[PDB]
Amino acid sequence: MIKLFSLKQQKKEAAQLRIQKDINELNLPKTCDISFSDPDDLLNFKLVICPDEGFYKSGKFVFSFKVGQGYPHDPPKVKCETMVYHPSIDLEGNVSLNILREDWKPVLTINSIIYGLQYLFLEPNPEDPLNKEAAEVLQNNRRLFEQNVQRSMRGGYIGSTYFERCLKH
Amino acid sequence: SKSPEELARYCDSLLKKSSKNPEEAELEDTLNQVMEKFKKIEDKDVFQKFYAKMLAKRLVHQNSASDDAEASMISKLKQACGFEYTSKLQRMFQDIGVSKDLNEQFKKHLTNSEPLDLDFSIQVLSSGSWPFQQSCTFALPSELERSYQRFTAFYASRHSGRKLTWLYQLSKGELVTNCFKNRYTLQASTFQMAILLYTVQQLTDSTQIKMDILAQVLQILLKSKLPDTLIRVNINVPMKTEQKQEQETTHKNIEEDRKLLIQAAIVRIMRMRKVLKHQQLLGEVLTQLSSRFKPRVPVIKKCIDILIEKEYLERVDGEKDTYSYLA
Amino acid sequence: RKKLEQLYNRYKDPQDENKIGIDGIQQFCDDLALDPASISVLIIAWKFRAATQCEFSKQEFMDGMTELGCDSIEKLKAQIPKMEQELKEPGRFKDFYQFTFNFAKNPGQKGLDLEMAIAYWNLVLNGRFKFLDLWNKFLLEHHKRSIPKDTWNLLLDFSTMIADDMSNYDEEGAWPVLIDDFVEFARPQIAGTKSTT
Amino acid sequence: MLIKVKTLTGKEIEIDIEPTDKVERIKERVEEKEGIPPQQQRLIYSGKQMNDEKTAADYKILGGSVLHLVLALRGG
Amino acid sequence: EVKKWNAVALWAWDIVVDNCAICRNHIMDLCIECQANECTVAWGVCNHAFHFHCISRWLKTRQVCPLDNREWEFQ
Ligand SMILES: [Zn+2]
Ligand SMILES: [Zn+2]
Ligand SMILES: [Zn+2]
């Protein structure tokens, strides 16, 4: 304990509030809902996207949002709790979305994140994949990628990976 | 073997207004040769940068000798550098045209209501696609004060929803002489012209001009004729120790854009790779980034050192000289 | 276990239940007879898995002492020579060294103040690094900003993997460019001298 | 119809629209008001990213409707 | 005197002016970092505004206006 001395001399004489503004102003699609375990603490919550259209149509995918104290300057850490067959999402549950890391700017909102997050399911892209096999099938065969995504959401094996059923009820 | 900043200066020299008036096929043949040289060049971004920056000054000064030549060049550049590069150029190109048209509309409007002493020709550019910069602190003494607010009238008549940021650093005007012995005529920068009614201390304040630039101006005024100290020729002239500054500037900006480019690339490759040794990383960053330029590896390394602190990648433990990707 | 609770109750401040104030931290150092700034106190803070300096959370203190199996200060002091001996064989000296980083900084920041990280280098890297003082002269001159985490971390591998005269050093290698900065600054002055160590 | 659009400054702007109008035009109206180039803009209407050459009647946008503006999105 | 003077100006977009886009606070109000305890306003050539504290930090990452990708410069 080095600087311990200095502190003593100075002894003798919420920053968000932003994520608050994000949440108040939040506008959710009919496909997306959010949950809070602790209504008092907004820096943690959950998001559920149920695509009504696309390959992932009729499916339930839940993401977790952890908002650091460096918000808006630091981006939220979000991960996909649902095991899914997607080029931009890995079995480890890491998400490849530009706004989440490099293209993040502190002019954005949780709303923004939600739109990009849904956008993955709307417009799945083989470019710079987290899952290479998924990106490869998406790349060469859309028919098979569709059949695959379906089998992945109803639950079943594709490869040696058992994909567990995520269907919305 | 010129090379790339100098090849750009070369092209400027070719396309600029000169006392010679180059014939068309000369222009075209030269330009074709320049592209031939350009294809051999390693760092093209510096070339593109200087070319654009100069092309700006040409267009804004009406100093192009041949318009169809410029147009042909931009054609050739688009063929090579692709659309994204020539987008800015092209918009610069058309924006000058609509600027000339708006200026003429103001000419038609100039001799009806209240014509005054100045024959007033202003060129206005987008917010915008033009590489220029905001003007310094200024004064705008005496008679010119009339035209400014006069100008600032009629836009409100056309579209009232726009704001004009005036570059006085790029603005020149003509003056004539009586008082001295032998008659001459002089074109001066508006900076030069504003000095005309004193000591540099109170002069700076009265003109509200920064002393740093003020000295740059008055040194070049003194080397022509006439801080606390008291004070077709033509006197508007580029300043020596300055405008070297803008070269440094330009090179800095190209360095920065190069950093962004590199970082992006290496992220791409790390994800693609998942893991790689330093050597292989550098190799790939190179072969991937070559067509635009060829980075000095201390730059590549400062980029890695940056993507470490931002937590894009980490060093594999126990393996020296090896990086792995994050999330 | 109640004994530990009473000792802790002697150290903690009345405002926070879990956090140990600085008045009590120097009390804690006084009873171990050491200096607050000592290497050993750092080793203790390392063993408690402390988050930051001058600051002991209840969980840190409690769990630290319980796996150190000490019911008192006097029982801790006797464990000090036990801790020092851990570094030697496969280490976990590295882990201690790297611990020092996040320990010494403020946990709102990714960097480390420059007058700091010198003090802790003169502490941990003392005797392991010859030109260490030269290094401190560097960046008191040529680099005025904070130390990056990876730079800190890698300085051990500098003090260990490469020679005193910096013969096997590569500037085209994987080192932090600040290490390269130092070496470039270094070789000129050191390549004309004969090491007696 | 006058549609409201939520910008990135944290406010809401009403703008003039015809249903036949292509949606890339609305981007330009938003540039005019908010000073953000139509080149980088993405319009989200109720959860989905609005197209460019497609029209506003293709999205069934009414005068009470609200648009969300966000920057470009890429998966990777 | 001047017979002929040709000048150069850039038309920039005029902006609503009301709200910091970083804190999503009001510009006249303190920035959110200062709200938890000198806080003033900064401008840009695009005519967008921010608190000093917000935009400075944004710049330390990258030199641009965050809203438009334009190079950042003060008034
Ligand atoms: Zn703010
Ligand atoms: Zn503030
Ligand atoms: Zn802006």
Image: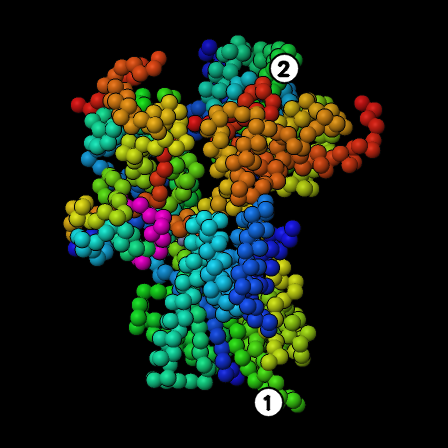
Q: Amino acid at mark 1?
A: Asn
| Secondary structure state at the residue bearing disc 1 | loop
User: Given the current orientation, which residue lies at the most extreme front position?
Assistant: B25
Residue A81 horizontal/vertical position (percent): 32, 23
Tag shown at residue B178:
1
Residue C57 horizontal/vertical position (percent): 47, 23
Q: Nearer the viewer, residue B279 or E62?
A: B279
Residue drawn 37% across the image and 81% down it: B110
For the record, the magenta segment spans D32-44
Which residue is identified by label 2? C87
Residue drawn 42% across the image and 75% down it: B148
Q: Nearer the viewer, residue C176 or A43?
A: C176
Q: Nearer the viewer, residue B22 or A154?
A: B22
Place residue A86 in its image quadrant: top left
For residue A93, say whether it is visible: no
Q: Is residue C82 left or right of residue B97?
A: right
Q: Where C24 sits versus C77, above or below?
A: below
* Disc 2 within 8 angstroms of ligand 2 (CB): no
Residue D3 horizontal/vertical position (percent): 20, 52
Task: Estimate the spatial distance between the alpha carbons at disc 2 and disc 1, rounded to whole Å.
Answer: 90 Å
Residue C5 horizontal/vertical position (percent): 46, 15
Is residue D41 within the magenta segment?
A: yes
Q: Is residue A2 left or right of residue A53?
A: right
Residue drawn 41% across the image and 63% down it: B95
Q: Nearer the viewer, residue E31 or A160?
A: A160
For residue B172, say whether it is visible: yes
Place residue A103 in its image quadrant: top left
Q: Where D75 sits versus C73, above or below?
A: below
10 Å neighbourhood of mark 2: few (<14), some, or many (≥20)? some
Q: Amino acid at mark 2?
A: Leu
Residue drawn 35% across the image and 79% down it: B108
**Label 2 is found on which chain of the structure?**
C
